[PDB]
Image (cartoon, coloured by chain):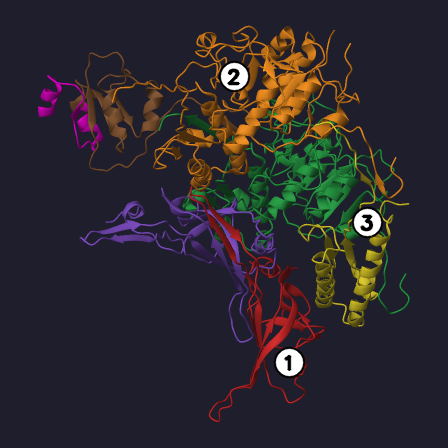
Chain colours: A green, B brown, C purple, D red, E orange, F yellow
Amino acid sequence: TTTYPGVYLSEDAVSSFSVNSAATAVPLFAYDSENTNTINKPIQVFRNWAEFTVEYPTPLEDAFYTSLSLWFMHGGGKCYLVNEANIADAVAQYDDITLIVAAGTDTTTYTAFTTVVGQGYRIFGLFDGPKEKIAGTAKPDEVMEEYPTSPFGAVFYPWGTLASGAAVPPSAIAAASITQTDRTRGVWKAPANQAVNGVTPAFAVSDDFQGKYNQGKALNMIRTFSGQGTVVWGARTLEDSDNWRYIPVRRLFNAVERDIQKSLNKLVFEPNSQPTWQRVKAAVDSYLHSLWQQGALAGNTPADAWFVQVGKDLTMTQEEINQGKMIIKIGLAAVRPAEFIILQFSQDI
Amino acid sequence: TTTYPGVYLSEDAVSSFSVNSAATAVPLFAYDSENTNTINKPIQVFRNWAEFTVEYPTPLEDAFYTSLSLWFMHGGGKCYLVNEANIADAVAQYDDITLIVAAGTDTTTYTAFTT
Amino acid sequence: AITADDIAVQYPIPTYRFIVTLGDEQVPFTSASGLDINFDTIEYRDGTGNWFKMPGQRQAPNITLSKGVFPGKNAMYEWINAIQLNQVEKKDIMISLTNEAGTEVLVSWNVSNAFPTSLTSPSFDATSNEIAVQQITLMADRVTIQTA
Amino acid sequence: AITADDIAVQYPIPTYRFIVTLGDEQVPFTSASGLDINFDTIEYRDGTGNWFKMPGQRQAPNITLSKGVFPGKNAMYEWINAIQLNQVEKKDIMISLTNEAGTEVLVSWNVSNAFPTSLTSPSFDATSNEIAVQQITLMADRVTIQTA
Amino acid sequence: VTSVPGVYIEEDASPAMSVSASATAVPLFVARFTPLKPELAGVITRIGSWLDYTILFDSNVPSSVVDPTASVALRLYFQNGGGPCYLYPLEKADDNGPLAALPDLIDEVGEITLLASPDPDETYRTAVYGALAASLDQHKGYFLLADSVNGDAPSAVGGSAQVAVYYPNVEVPPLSLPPSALIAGVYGKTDGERGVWKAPANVVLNGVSDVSVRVTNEQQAELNPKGINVIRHFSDRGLVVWGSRTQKDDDDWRYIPVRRLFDAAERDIKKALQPMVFEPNSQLTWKRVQTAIDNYLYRLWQQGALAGNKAEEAYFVRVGKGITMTQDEINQGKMIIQVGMAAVRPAEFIILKFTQDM
Amino acid sequence: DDDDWRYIPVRRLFDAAERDIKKALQPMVFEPNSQLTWKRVQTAIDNYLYRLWQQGALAGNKAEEAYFVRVGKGITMTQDEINQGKMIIQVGMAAVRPAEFIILKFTQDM
């Protein structure tokens, strides 16, 4: 309470984090329906930290609160809390959600994530792993039977134990290395070696434990190091096919398919004829040359990188011009991370 | 075998030579037909060293192997191994061969060179 | 006919395309100079006429870099502010002449243990249409040229 | 499409728009330079070959400001005239690159304890169409860069 | 019990012990350590100094004809050159449960270099040396310090280059200790003062007085063409570790300082290239990795580690696409680097050849 | 009896620093509540806390371990709080505690 025009003093212990967001990381912190600590608003938007401690002024410990608090302290712009039985309703309604993070949540977020992928909203899910320790006699095909076999998700096993002692769901640690990588290196670089500060894993993972969980369903360890501490260590999705392995090339094609979808809806009600098929083809081509130039594609000429076709005998038919349908088929080559660095030493010079 | 995403260590003794070729030196390392150590492909192309020790992963001592190994360590681009009874067939077919080198070979390479 | 794959072998390299690897990160710079290799000279003369000329010991390079001021976080202030009487994070500098795509090195100048000794502010002038350019000078021990 | 809110994030900053906070007041200046961060160099060599290169102690900045002569009261003469053998009102200098409206800081150069050491008169010339510009030089102890 | 803000006086304290700092000799002593609080019973704990040992573990442990020797073996470790000193308390020998889980707990901690289990029982060490023998040939950089029983290798680790045996039991004022707790100390002393390329074989052992068996030259002459590395007694000097061979009889990996130079260089290159993992596998990254190895190998050569005179005779680093790789190997996401070095071998034989003709 | 405010010199350091910051920011009252003023207030506190650290008052080794000053609009405030005419600043410090117990522990074994 402020009364007189002077300078006021207080010692109520508060904290406040700044905002250093990126536009390609707008998550969906899904929480369980079996929870009375949350505000009964089913969907709510949190643009920064100073608004999140107005709705929730006291520090909790629950899995939705150590997930948002570890989000906002690494930048992080707006982000959502939705019930686990309403995430299909909120993806379809706010139009800028680029991530679904299961903040200590399963068995129906896994279901309703598979709902929105078949509807094709270009989302990328971030799931969790086991909360108690995997043994070592685990037979990994029995642990990752639960998880979807879609290329739009990743799992990230070791749970967090941030400085207050509370548990962090490892969908929030893995979404904290996506804020700091889309800001810094872009969406095409793998989110792995980015250091997330103020958290420590609950358990420890040896190199020989991660080696059986690397191929297949790709459990994506969180590991601490001397130097770059408590990074996430592994950047693979839930499918080991040779094009939708590697988390970054999937999010590189989400943002390509969506920045061309939002740049070419401003060309509706044009005549569906040959001048329109040109200014499609030079609007796609101008976008991808801004993208090839900042190191996001592969090949050292723009003919090496992308192609695009739209037209009469290329990709459409006269049955489809007369009912409106414009089909724009693009093909583009992305880069791959260097995952294994083999040092082979010798004795002779 | 690579399993986990870290940094790997090994001590298997290998060698590797770089490529500093010239376009006017594409030889023809003709070898004898009386030889079972070679791969039974009659004509084969070796663009660099790292492809030549895939076909022949162990160090031999025969006259076709000390000829190619002394080729690639001085630059050397692509180059050919052909049987001594097939060099007239390979000169007429690849169109960039500028040299015929008899790698420990006579009495029919001398004949088919005059062809 | 010059067939531009031959231009990539036997024509010289210009100086406008370069990547500066600064420790473990790439930082975009505008200028880069002073990556010299200088020796001293030992001399000895006797009365008979023998002059003996010898290379001395090589002295330290002084590398100066300059980049523009951006609205975010100043990474070059954060590395010259972390000086405590001896203690500086030395970094490895790599300045590589690159192709136009930016993905392969033509020739590189490597610098072993560099630490900042100066950082100049931009010159503020109300009658000038220029960009705010900081200029950092570094001091190291060795300059290495790798060519590939 | 570059959408100018992205220009305010990732394009560099020019040098023609700046606010100089001089103690607790804003004074309009034309130029401002010399806000450097300079260190000295310690060196040590032994006979085995170890060269030890270290940052020394940082020396004082010398900041020079220049503004025009206005018909009112001279605030820079009133601060260099109040010298009594040691005694000068030290001031905090803040030179902030600002937006075009003048209401928010892009990046700032802070200067801790500055006091005037010189004040030059304008050059009077009967054949010149110029403005009378005084140039004051300051001496301080620390230069700080805050970015926000 | 301090409440008055003055100065307090106690009169029967024990003298404290100093600890050094090293990064190339961090051992894992597997012995019969008795904890105070029982949560650290089957795990590996870090013991940064002797003061950390007295708080976490029971350091007195009164005897009953059996005598506790695990706390005595660590005091001789810190007297001979301390370290971060990981411990694994393993009570009895025949529990094949915790011994099967031992090599998986070592990999979870990042920084173990030496093993060196300091226990006076003979069948206790054989169960430990057999459980650790499979982890020595997996390129992880460990180095076992075994102990001979009557003049031969303990046969769980026969001829691997990662093993250094040390024969004579060393007596303390008299209980006889296996020498591995002391030799793990003198590795950290030698590496801090001289480097890993120096042979750790002229260090006088602090603490202890005399060995259990005084070894002659003629029985060392049948032992030193194996890796047995006898602790000798010299009258002017005391107890000197005398021998720097491994179990491998090859010309390459015969000596300890040649072997531990390559283990330490591979460990420090590996810690330097892990920031370059998940980078784009392009030619720009391959040159950033080549320079990071070339900067490391240059500052080993200029401090005397590598045996060269030109720095092109000491080492080389090679990476490329025509060299060391194929295009099918980039596409599966790996880079292959060829690093070579040249180490110097110690002088272990001096022949004098006197005469009186001139 | 709290661990924070147990000692007199820790308590009177915070009382004296809050008193001298308050005397320094009263010229910045009735200024325009804009982002230019918030940086002028942040620097006036940062200049004060730096010259406490360099004379030994604060327990730090880097001057980022001794103190911090935070002000902004997304940080420490909301837009509804600027409109009612106030600025909110978060200042933290780290003081050093005195040695009041000395234990000698004599012996005669060496």
Marks 2, 1 in one chain: no
**Would you call the spot at circle 2 few (<14 residues within 10 Å), some (14-19), or many (20 or more)?**
many
Q: Are marks 1 and 3 in contact (CB under 8 Å)?
A: no
* Residue C117 to residue F101: above or below: below
Which residue is under mark 1? D80
The residues bearing labels 2 and 1 have C-alpha atoms spaced at a distance of 77 Å
Image quadrant holding the C terminus of chain A, namely top left
Q: Amino acid at mark 3?
A: Thr
Tell whether F87 sits left or right of C44.
right
Please provide percent x and percent y for residue C112. Answer: 45, 45
Which residue is under mark 2? E164
Tell me the subunit letter for badge 1: D
- Asked whether residue A135 appears in the rendered view, the answer is no
Q: Nearer the viewer, residue B109 or E174?
A: E174
Task: Looking at this view, name the residue that lies furthest to the bottom.
Answer: D126
Q: Amino acid at mark 1?
A: Ile
Chain part drawn in magenta: B89-115
- Magenta segment: does it hold F91? no
Instruction: Give the number of the disc on residue A53.
Output: 3
The residues bearing labels 2 and 3 have C-alpha atoms spaced at a distance of 61 Å
**Would you call the spot at circle 3 few (<14 residues within 10 Å), some (14-19), or many (20 or more)?**
some
